[PDB]
Image 1 (tube, helix red, strand yellow):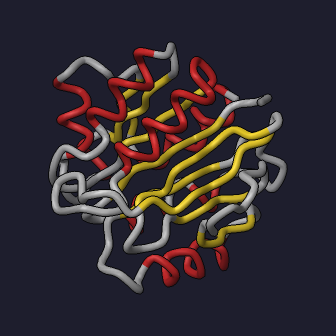
Image 2 (cartoon, helix red, strand yellow):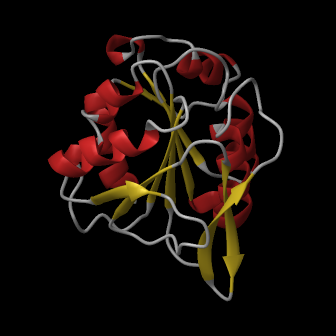
Length: 189
């Protein structure tokens, strides 16, 4: 497997912060982006359309068995944890139906666990606004493999819970307001 990957975790106010990130990335962004946004079943598709309409990158819902490619932003669908698997030098998504991690599924911790193991030091985690601690254990894995972690600054958060939890463990390499995140991503890849 070549290149890097960006895995974003978000909850409360997630869409608002993503609006300051995704639309500001070039069509030729070299790393595939995966977004795990906490939301009741049946709403993740609305998010895909919302972001696809304002972005140069192609935003869609992640599909089972689909190949993870650059130039795309994949939104995790409801009812399943979004996994990643490496096969013959390529990376594919898989819908896992194991227990809820928190009272949440998909949980960004599951996606990051899989992504980190595959991409290792080339893994980039972004933990945005939201309640709870989802993204913290996932950030641990990312750092354990030499990856990089970005936590959203309180300034642009609706709820400074998820990013704060990541920061308090010492897992954040960068603490940035949503609008500065796209710029940081562009220089890291």
